[PDB]
Amino acid sequence: YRIXSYDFXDKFKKLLRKAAG
Amino acid sequence: YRIXSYDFXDKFKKLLRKAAG
Amino acid sequence: YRIXSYDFXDEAEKLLRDAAG
Amino acid sequence: YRIXSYDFXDEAEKLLRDAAG
């Protein structure tokens, strides 16, 4: 899932992890 | 925030609402 | 990942695929 | 919207802008 060459998919998955325990 | 003509931004905002109280 | 009983995690993945292909 | 004290809401908006323009 990318916008151009930016991997939104990857960052969103990392954000879900960051936001959790 | 769109992928092509799809409004991801709008659907994501609706999902945050659906997921909450 | 969930909010209460709401499957936020899975719903977000569904949105990612629905907004893409 | 937050997860505990984590500002999930705001972090997601930041990600949306970071992945775009």
Image (spheres, coloured by chain):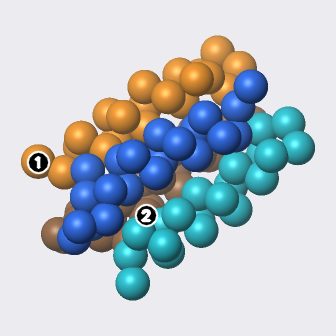
Chain colours: A brown, B blue, C cyan, D orange
Residue A11 visible within the image: yes
Parent chain of label 1: D
* Viewer-proximal residue among D1 and A2: D1
| Residue A3 in which image quadrant | bottom left
Dot 2 surroundings within 10 Å: few (below 14), some, or many (20 or more)? some
Q: Which mark is residue D21?
A: 1
The residue drawn where x is 48% and y is 66% is C16
Dot 1 surroundings within 10 Å: few (below 14), some, or many (20 or more)? few
The residue drawn where x is 70% and y is 31% is B20
The answer to whether residue D7 is left or right of residue C7 is left
Parent chain of label 2: A
Judge whether A18 appears above or below B6 on screen: above
* Viewer-proximal residue among B10 and A19: B10
The residue drawn where x is 43% and y is 25% is D10
Q: Are marks 2 and 1 on the same chain?
A: no
Give the Cα distance between marks 2 and 1: 16 Å
Number of residue marks: 2
The answer to whether residue B5 is left or right of residue C18 is left
Residue D19 visible within the image: no
The answer to whether residue C14 is left or right of residue D10 is right
Residue C2 place in picture, x, y as percent: 78, 46
